[PDB]
Image: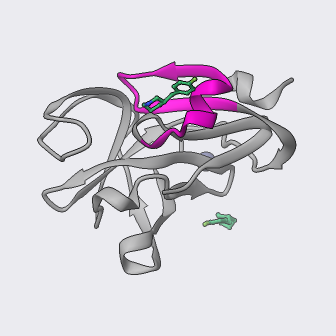
Amino acid sequence: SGAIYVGNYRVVNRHLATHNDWANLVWEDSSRDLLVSSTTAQGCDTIARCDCQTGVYYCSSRRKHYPVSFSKPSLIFVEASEYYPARYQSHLMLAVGHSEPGDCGGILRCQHGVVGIVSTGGNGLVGFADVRDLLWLDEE
Ligand SMILES: Fc1ccc(C[C@@H]2CCCNC2)cc1
Ligand SMILES: Fc1ccc(C[C@H]2CCCNC2)cc1
Ligand SMILES: [Zn+2]
């Protein structure tokens, strides 16, 4: 689990979005595993605006932060988890690292702020849904 809180926005994995998230839907993309809902309380997170390929992610299944090198956001085929089947995901970044289902929502961060959230895993890789393209998260 886990979310990003920036202004009046909550960013979550689309597959973990709550009834409240969907009731206050701002934007969702099934291909990206992202949903943004509106919040009454102002969030304090900063979204990274950059093309860093290094950062640190929180891995709840190890209660540890790991430094990783990660690929630029791409269209990637993802093999069978349990929440999703096998299928294709856009704006996805991979690193070598530990990821289990419940690690989704772990934040990946660089010096510039939040890069993305854990979204996929398995075969010794971790996949992160990029948010750095969502410039609109930084206003109203
Ligand atoms: F009125 C409402 C409000 C939110 C949901 C959305 C949830 C999301 C998970 C799947 N069950 C539905 C439905 C109806
Ligand atoms: F998890 C992290 C990782 C790094 C920073 C800090 C910056 C500044 C020092 C070098 N670049 C990184 C913040 C949160
Ligand atoms: Zn950066």
Q: Position of 138 compared to 106: left or right?
A: right
Q: Quadrant of residue 51?
A: top right
- Total numbered badges shown on the rendered structure: 0
Q: Position of 134 compared to 84: left or right?
A: right
Q: Is residue 132 visible?
A: no
Q: Is residue 133 magenta?
A: no
The residue lying at 18 percent from left, 47 percent from top is 81
Q: Position of 23 compared to 72: left or right?
A: right
Where residue 99 appears, x then y in whole percent?
A: 30, 62
Name the one closer to the observer, 128 or 20. Answer: 20
Image quarter of the C terminus: top right
- Give the residues in magenta: 16-37
The residue lying at 28 percent from left, 62 percent from top is 100
The residue lying at 37 percent from left, 79 percent from top is 62
Where residue 7 appears, x then y in whole percent?
A: 82, 38
Where residue 24 appears, x then y in whole percent?
A: 68, 26
Q: Is residue 26 magenta?
A: yes
